[PDB]
Amino acid sequence: SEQSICQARAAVMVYDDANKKWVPAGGSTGFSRVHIYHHTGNNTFRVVGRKIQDHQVVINCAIPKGLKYNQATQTFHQWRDARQVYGLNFGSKEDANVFASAMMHALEVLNS
Image 1 (cartoon, rainbow, N blue to C red):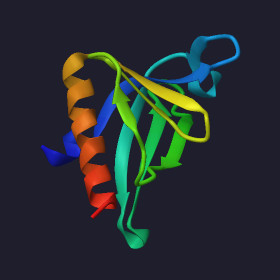
Image 2: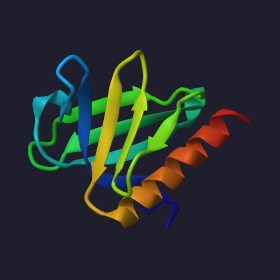
Image 3: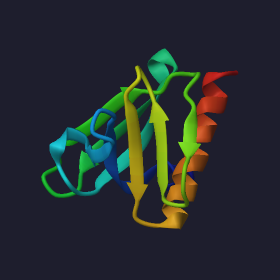
Image 4: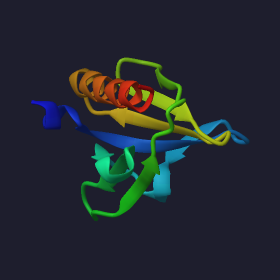
């Protein structure tokens, strides 16, 4: 379904460039439920990630229309914003593919 396409479980990651290491976003190992939400009132999209166990929000960001979203592997996607690199480590290839499709749709909307 469309709404099911708009979320997926993944570990949210950030890249420590100085030490060349991927680390958990928010410092919290584990998967989050990662959603793309269409905030229609101001015509924005947000990516919101909340940890599956403790339910802490680890990412909550507006998607910029010029985002370069890279599908680096079958289960790991990444993007930059502000020289800060974020990643999503999906639990499965199928969920990675559906979330990518959701992101690409959001970017199409934001650029029309």
